[PDB]
Image 1 (cartoon, rainbow over the protein chains, first blue to last red):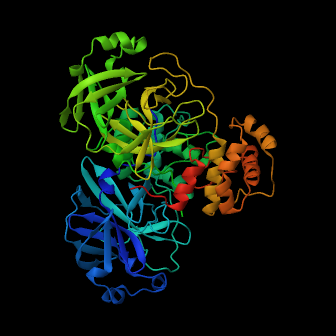
Image 2: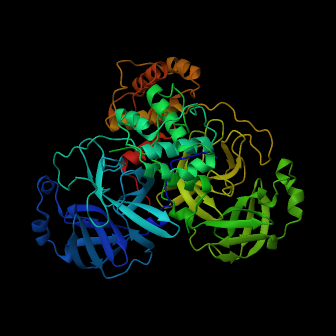
Image 3: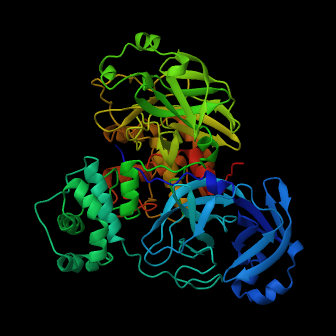
Length: 306
Length: 306
């Protein structure tokens, strides 16, 4: 029993982290096979970030201008190219620790683990979600760009995020591993403001199922609802509209607990309208939305990775 | 910016996890040098757990009765001994992935990372604290015993916890790596109830400093207090008494923010008496007590491990 915000084991990703320095800027890179991936703003000074022309700035950079260090050893850069907002630095040595991996572009509402790194060295691991406004609420200081987000299915690491930017409001923006930003954000130090931080309804419901499986049952009420009636309440509280696709995804948790999805929706509706009255659910005083239905099943079934 | 519940990178510990089977019971072991450490209740059936005589049960076990598997390969058990509540299984091969390590017995209030494992395979990593009642609030299913808790300082893993038991109330109990339980708990399936779940005051204060460093400043008030006056409020709310030792430990965070420790205490006192009025601090609707002052400094300074 017990339900915790749980990250994936990070060892497979630790073995891929390197330090990348270009001129005076140092950040992290991801070394997979004979390629190191990093944010293209490694080529920028802080002055450059205000209005960078990346193609022009890149002209002044050769292979030998990218210093790549894995622990205490250099890697030799034999080619480089810009793909969207990432650089691909070809090195002469394939990473002997390369795991099985894929690059995936995730949907808003999906979760992943972040290995926060500085100077190519892992500092910590935590769980994030891609918010509906395409930001993430991470923990990133200077030096952390190029840290990655990932999921693991057995022995395959699916990389889905690379950190690039901190917005003036303290939330975070980045790209997939093909270098395309999530949402409308750009790698320029400008006025970029995030849209509404909407709550991920299907994730709240999954977490309520996790609470029931763990004995936290006080919020179960005598009511049910419909999708359209629930969504009238979802909209007022800045919750994502619940769809039939979401109902289908919650099917297994509904079967395990014997609580119909729409009955759980009516419980959530009462929590939104009445608050929690100073009570807690799984040790939280607010409605948690960064566990997916898949996250709940994994943590409740003990799925492992090798 | 951003502050997250952050675990240590788990790769150094992943390489030490093995599966231990004795008879029909399978759990996890920790392989360091040529010794595998695991809970002694690996020798018990579920019936045995009601009133086990471990010395008697162990008589019926020989080296060859302990099946130890690292991934897909057996390890050969060449000796075994009981130390308190752990078994030490001597194997004929030193773990080639053994990190620099120490065994430490932690104090209540200190935090650590848990690598939850099943059948010797890591499933996830999360952050815990040793509660003042000597329980931990973890996430452990059947199969998870022998999972360990640890801290890392640079390249040295300090192992501090091994999971043994789930209490009927759903909280968790275990030992240090010398096999001595934290608190009064025993490895027997009996009525063991936890004492008061007291809040770790020095950790709440550290987290309030983390909030200020991140721009969450609404709870700063115009008041100060004294240790004795604060502790009159701490006692009413089941908070640990704050001591001068705690004040000294918070010194660096006080210096960085310019907020005197006793001024932060008066802010906390108002939060305890008035509640948070539906507001949040670092995304939490309650007062968080599982970050130590050291955890805050590390996460706020970007300390790394290699």
